[PDB]
Structure formats: C-alpha cells, structure tokens
Length: 115
Length: 114
Length: 114
Length: 113
Image (cartoon, rainbow over all chains, first blue to last red; front, side, top):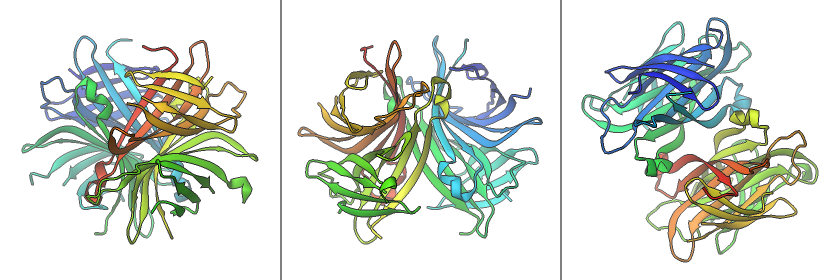
C-alpha cells in the first residue's frame, strides 16, 4: 500500500512504514541528509475510489545538521498502477516575533513509486 | 516547555509530550479523542527565535472516522505567555475529480492558559 | 461597509473603493511605500449572517522600488461593531527554476476600521 | 508573454491582458471577470515574473459567494507557463469560518492539454 519507498518530483526520497494502528514512521532523505519522519494516516479508508488521507512531519535536525525548521505534509494516497501521494506542505522555520510574518512557506509535492 | 496541556483559540485541547530527541506524542481532544504524532527542533537557536515544530492527527479513532487528516506546522514561543502559533492543512480523501477541493488551510494559536 | 480605510494588525494600511460591479481598487501603504491594489468582491452576498467574499492583489513595485514580488489576500469581510476583514495571503517572489520551491510564503492578517 | 490565452491542467481557460503599468485584466472561464497585478520590470537574472489575480465567482448567471486568488510567476522559455498557488474563500458565518478557505496550485500553459 503506502509502505515502501517514494520518490518526489525533484530528488528527495522517503521510506515509510504504515502501521496497522494508523502510524507512519520512516526516514526522509534530502546520512548527513537523512531525517526522521513521523505521521498518521486513515487505516480504514473508503473503497469508493477516494484516496487515503495522511500527513507527516520532518524536523530538519539530525546528528550532523539543524536547519531550525520543520515541514509538514498533508495529502493523500491514490493506489493503482499509477500510485501517487499528492501533497501540500508547510515549511516553518524558527524566527523572532518580528519575522514571524515571513516564517512559513507553502508548496506542493507529488511522490511516486518509481524514479 | 512544549510538554503539557494546550488549548486552541476556539475550544480544542491537546496534551503533548516532547521526547529528548525531537519526538512529539500525545492526544488531541472520549469519542473526541485522537492520537497525534510529530517532531520538533530539539536544539533551537539561542537568538530569541522560536522552536519549529509540526504534528499530524488522522481523524480516526475507535469510534469515528472522517477520512481526513490535519497537519499543523509552526513554532513554540517562550514568553510571558508561552504560545504555539501554527498554520494548518486539513486534507480529506476525495476521488481524483474532486481533488482540487480536498484541502483546507487555516491557522491557530495555542496557550497553556485557558 | 468595505469602502474606506483599513488597518492591519502589523502597522500597514489600505484604502479601498468597492465599486458596484464587484471591483476593488485602492492603494496599500510616504510615497515610496505606496502601491496599487486591485481586486474583486461578492457584490451580492447572502443575508444569513455569512461574510462577504473578496480578494485582492498587490505587486511590490512602484515608481521608486521593485521587490519583484506580489501578494494576494483571500478572505472575507465581516461587518457590524468590530467590522473586520479576515484574510489568508500568499506572497510570491520571482525566482529561477531552481529556487521555485521556496518562492511562496503563506500567512494571515486581520484588518479593522480602527 | 503574459498577454494571451492560457489553459490550466483541469480545462479552465483564462484570457488576460498585461498592461503598461503592471495591470492584469481579463476573463476566467460561464465567464468571470478577473483582475490582478504583475511585476512590469522583472529581474534580468533569469528570474520569473511575479504576478497575481483575483476572481469573484459572481456574474449575471450565478453567484457562489466565493473568491479565489492566484499567486505565482510567469516563466518564458520554449514553452511558457504560469505556476500558481491559490486560495479559495467562501462567505460563512463566524462558527464556520474555520473551514472557509481551500488551498491549491494551478499551472497554466499557452497550449491546451
């Protein structure tokens, strides 16, 4: 299903394990560039062709690096021969109160099972 | 600092534990109880910046399932009033044709008071 | 309700005229910090107590400066005592293909008449 | 290269004129009035051209009590395109304001897919 390796549009890779309990655990790779991922997903989705909702978070700190920022992906898994996870993300960095207005970026990413 | 009980600027409540190397665990509020999990910057800057964090809640518990998930992205702020300022994304499972309307966006502030 | 001067929580200011077929025109703000705004709003909202949908755009260029960016605000007008415009915004900066992933900030602002 | 007729991946069409002073005027497709701004003097460094516009979903046939704003940048190239992120807000009561806004992304090209 979701368990496995996913490739994003521009290079990044993640390995995720989708637990029976609805937990998402894995690693995201931008080892200097490997980071822990953690999330949740709908473990009892609809079969009417709806995708499966999920989200996950990466804090960009590891034993070598720290960008003082975090990304959260919200989106959905669509199975099939053309399996994909379509997401929108929010990147939030630590800032002072005075730069909190410019603290968050928004984007989107598509992950597929090959590439 | 992050560990403890927080209240939403409307009325929800969440209980968090922050693990020494960046894990966020706890629950977002009986039938209204859901698991949350996330990560945080466990070695933030010392310049007065806040602490970047995120978490996810999938809206399924042993009683209900909305077929959707929400992620909060933000930062913890130490001050007179410690706060967590977030922006959030709620994605619902949809067929492909309705994907364009699958995701809500909003923001929220949590405080330990109230 | 919308025509007039609005102040955002952060110090900035905008003067708008809401025309009769949904046009929004005005300036966002000394001269060096004034910029043209243009937008649209629902000139016939429901009367169920719902807010009035609107939006507008500002590119950050004037005769004196050019940040090579633009902001869009999407939100609603809520009249009455504390009349307010509640918005979410996107700021996009022109980037090369390579930095496009970090081209768009998101946030929120609330405008009041005082 | 902004002036012209553009196509979005889901079939939507927008006709727009880019004027002298950074104004954007046109129609989104029945049809809805659009207006926006663009950077009339972009960087030389191969950066894209920042831009944005708005549509309120009311015309003479219907009104959805909503508005969408697209924020993005134009990239010339052998196949020009406009990459955008968008927010769609509906009028709602206070109690429902929390779900009043949708967020998405849209790519327009001068060729119809």
